[PDB]
Amino acid sequence: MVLSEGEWQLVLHVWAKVEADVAGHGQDILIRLFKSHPETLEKFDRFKHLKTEAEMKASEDLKKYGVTVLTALGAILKKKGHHEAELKPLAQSHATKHKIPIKYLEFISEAIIHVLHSRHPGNFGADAQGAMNKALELFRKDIAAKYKELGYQG
Ligand code: HEM
């Protein structure tokens, strides 16, 4: 797939708002993911024992990971599709060490779109949400193709 420059503009305009508070957005997104799809919390040995949202909110480890995820994804989005280098080490670790099925990447993509819609309604109208969705589909598609080269396709 290929996004037009106007679609990348929409994606990078709302991402610039997320970047004013990377740790807060990271928390919201992961909590939305774990509340919606609790099976995903099991991949985290660091904090799969968390039982409630309150515990999740108070976890410093969870907030750190949120920053890790959003910083890596922000660097990929800013490439505007030229992200081959960035995707290599990510696809290897998620396919061979963590073992994250593509389906889980779809789940976190939904959680991102939900939180942007909640926090940034004025910069996340239908067109900007369609463009973010396209940017995340592109990301999943390219990661899925690398999983396959790596021997995992999950
Ligand atoms: C937007 C999508 C995602 C991005 C950009 C991302 C990025 C990262 C980065 C940069 C790391 C640390 C370096 C490395 O291990 O490669 C990491 C580690 C990890 N990721 Fe993610 N990730 C994403 C989705 C997921 C999902 C959906 C799951 C699980 C349901 C997952 C589970 C893990 C695990 C278990 C670790 C190890 C954490 C540790 O113990 O510190 N990732 N991820």
Image (tube, rainbow, N blue to C red):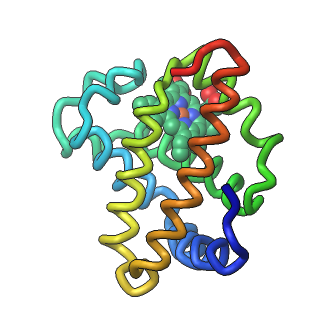
Residue positioned 59% across, 74% down in the render: 16
Placement of 62 over or under 100, stated as above or below: below
In the orientation shown, which residue stands out farthest toward the front? Answer: 1
Residue positioned 77% across, 59% down in the render: 79
Task: Give the image location of residue 125, x and y in percent.
Answer: 40, 81
Placement of 11 over or under 151, stated as above or below: below
Task: Give the image location of residue 88, x and y in percent.
Answer: 76, 32
- Which quadrant of the structure image shows residue 104? top left
Task: Give the image location of residue 121, x and y in percent.
Answer: 35, 81
Q: Quadrant of the N terminus?
A: bottom right
In the orientation shown, which residue stands out farthest toward the bottom? Answer: 122
Number of numbered tags placed on the structure image: 0
- 9 vs 60, nearest the viewer: 9
- Which quadrant of the structure image shows residue 143? top right
Residue positioned 58% across, 25% down in the render: 94
Task: Give the image location of residue 36, x and y in percent.
Answer: 23, 42
Residue positioned 58% across, 78% down in the render: 10
Placement of 101 over or under 108, stated as above or below: above
Placement of 78 over or under 103, stated as above or below: below
Q: Is residue 109 left or right of residue 86?
A: left
Q: Quadrant of ligand 1?
A: top right
Q: Is residue 46 left or right of residue 72?
A: left
